[PDB]
Image 1: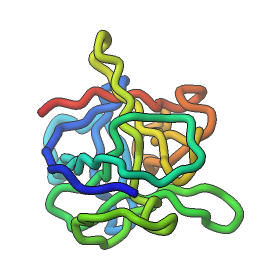
Image 2: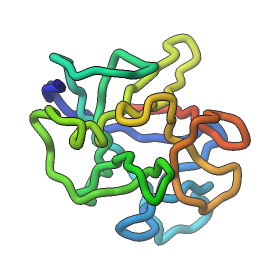
Image 3: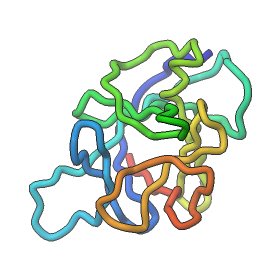
Image 4: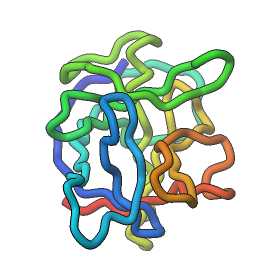
Length: 159
């Protein structure tokens, strides 16, 4: 279904200028990181994939990516927890091939708006669900089917 093409490292902020920090090995939180800080901003290793597949279904395309938490040996994934879609961080190595519905948990569609300089990330495993931050500081990064509605689901990436 997906085949690895390369990885590139990016800085990331949400549209309100919050960055990510890894508050514990299972929780990424978003905050205005400022003044003095012990806290190390998270960068992303974005692994770009090419399809040979697999569908369906979705609501998105056409840059499938995995999102590595640079330096911490984690990748973001979307899974069901209880009965709710959930963003989690998993100890996973770099995946050359994503060729099962299980491994599709790691794939997001990077949706850039070339004009505005902005990006959304839609889950491939949970179409219509997007990576989001709270309007409040120090809350976990998560996923939502209401992108940008009393959350922020729009980011600025920089190489």
